[PDB]
Every structure is written in C-alpha cells, then in structure tokens.
Amino acid sequence: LGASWHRPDKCCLGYQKRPLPQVLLSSWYPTSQLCSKPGVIFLTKRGRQVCADKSKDWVKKLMQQLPVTAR
C-alpha cells in the first residue's frame, strides 16, 4: 500500500474477450512491459477503457484503424 495509485496496473490480466466496434472507439494506449501479460487498452470516444491483446484479431484491426494515445 502507500500511494498504490502510483502503480498503474494497466497490465490487465484479462482482456475484453469480445470484439468492439470502432464506430465509437477513439484510440488505444500500450501498457508496460514489466507485466506477466501486458497488452493494450482502448479508450473509447466517450465510452470507457478496454483491455485487449494485439494478438487478438479485432484488436489488431483497431490498431491499424486507430493511431495511438500519444500525449
């Protein structure tokens, strides 16, 4: 504990598991590499974040459909 927030557990242990539509998606940001199984989270336009693994199929298309959260 102690400012645990300082630790961004973005390395979602599990992923969406389902293919979401880019019709409402915005972009996607990659997690750290110091994880047991880090992938990439998708930040919908106005929806929410979604952990996914580029390894997937729909997650791959999105990567090409969207750029990446850089800021």
Image (cartoon, grey):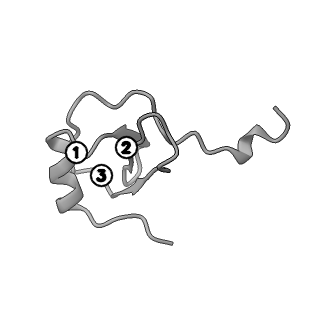
Which residue has dot 2 on it? 39
Dot 1 falls on a residue whose secondary structure is helix
Q: Residues within 10 Å of mark 3 (few under 14, many from 20)?
A: many
- Considering only order in the chain, which callout, 1 or 3, is on the residue closer to the N terminus? 3
Residue type of the residue flagged with mark 2: Gly
> Residue 41: x, y in percent?
40, 46
Disc 2 vs disc 1: Cβ atoms closer than 8 Å?
yes
Structural crowding at the residue carrying mark 1, measured as other residues with C-alpha within 10 Å and reported as few (<14), some (14–19) or many (≥20)? many
Among the 4 quarters of the image, the one containing residue 56: top left
Which tag, 2 or 3, sits closer to the chain's start?
3
CA distance separating discs 2 and 3 = 17 Å
Q: Secondary structure at mark 2?
A: loop
> Mark 3 sits on what residue?
25
Q: Quadrant of residue 16?
A: top left
Between circles 3 and 1, the one closer to the viewer is 1
Q: Residue at x 29, y 41 (%)?
A: 53
Disc 1: which residue: 59
Q: Provide residue 19's location: percent of width, then percent of height.
A: 20, 35
Residue 15 drawn above or below residue 42: above
Q: Is residue 69 above or below residue 35?
A: below
Cα separation between marks 3 and 1: 12 Å
